[PDB]
Image (cartoon, rainbow over all chains, first blue to last red; front, side):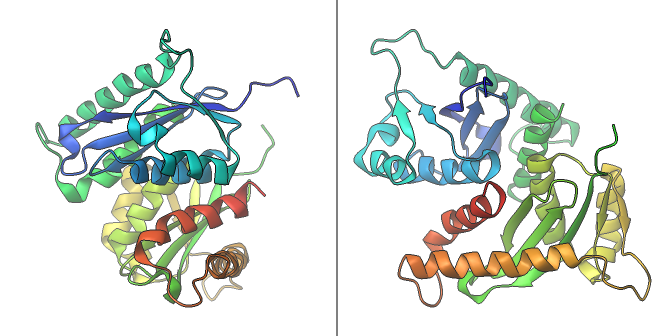
Length: 146
Length: 146
């Protein structure tokens, strides 16, 4: 009733231990702080939509999503995908202050956990392709359900 | 405190509109009724573990999981994966009554929603490979967050 508004912050961050699909799309729900992450081979408009599709099935549909002015976020294709869902989009204050400090903190936490868990299993550099999936799920589990 | 126990029921069901990865692994959390589904090319022990890895990141770690006696569920590899996580496994009453009526109801609901949504987008038969992912996420969203 008076609970937090369902606004998300989403960003892409690069992680060479997950190559070839080293681009991680990360979404923080600012109401509950849950984190959602997916892996992509390239940072395109289609990869952001695929990421939000998965986040929507996991967290439910938000009232709005805050992103930066990356092209994969302000392109026509992406503005139409968001309108088809009824989700408002804002790139925040124009010149900002980066009102997406949350996703940026999530990004560092996420890369740390990936590195500790991978090193925990003997992978000092790249994680074998076949192990990437479970480790990513595992880092996401440790970050949400502490 | 007195809330429901966190027990899951999981099963695989076949869906030719999602081919080539037409095997759907579906998990119902009997405490909250949420549904989790993932797509696989073959029904193996490794595909069940990958499915639960994703369900664990989405729903948190359960106290137990109820399955049937499929080999991909009672194999050594799978019993060890479950022990590594500390999750109890039961195949229920031996000769049963099928105390996994829930996952079976979820399976029919899920296949219906997939068919209505696909037909809604003009796909009377197989769904194009590139559209499978979002539609699956979409059916999962409609079934959880009604």
